[PDB]
Length: 129
Image (tube, rainbow, N blue to C red):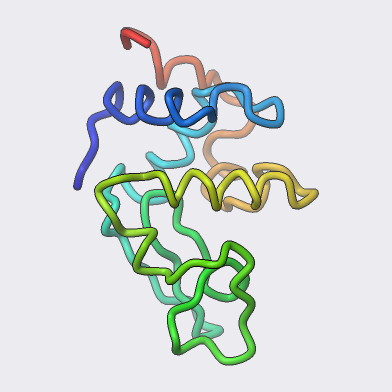
């Protein structure tokens, strides 16, 4: 599923991401924007053989199991395919673990390089939340 900006903001909010670990909603939307273009089905292969999955491009190297990432952890206890669903529940639950991991939202490269330190409130402007 390709979400719209406000549809995603809503979805995230209902799932408890607004201000989760101090990250305003605008951050999560911005990060989804650049990581996956709001497409739940987004996959991307890394040079280390790991793959990134779903709206928040969660990495198989640590967080989910895809059966083809040797010596990887499955810290979220999910198959990676679960990250690609039209229901973002699993992607949100796993993201909450990731952001708690110590580096905050800096775990998301596109957040760091394109969202961080910007006016992220612009991502939710005009939405009915």
